[PDB]
Image (cartoon, rainbow, N blue to C red; front, side, top):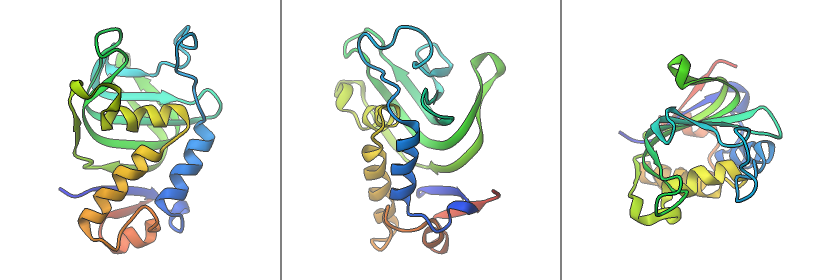
Length: 183
């Protein structure tokens, strides 16, 4: 199946690129780096975790922005290649108001704005921190969504070369890729 996109009607006239650049500016950089992961405030979490699961979720420490990555995901922690996320990334949901976690049966994003599904990404452990899945998710943690933008640009061009991250959500809905959701 081709990339599927949802978007709240209030973003109908935005391009994908402008939405993601703006979301990244609100989320900011959670500072997930050596000496700066000292407690659970900026780790995020897996369901079921602690290091693997079908969801990885993180809330911003600068805003209420949050995302959930869905698929079949694995984090190496200290194991070579250290601090690598690899595996199957099917979906990214972005917005605000993260709730839940492993103990309550799953994460939910109560103010989801936009989602991207059927991403078809599957990165092997061998690529380490240069894997596409790793770069996509670490970009969302660190205030730079350029890796996600590039993957969406390629998936959209695969549907039709007239579609891109510079398409508005409106235009993607007319093309049958995107679907407006209630605001």
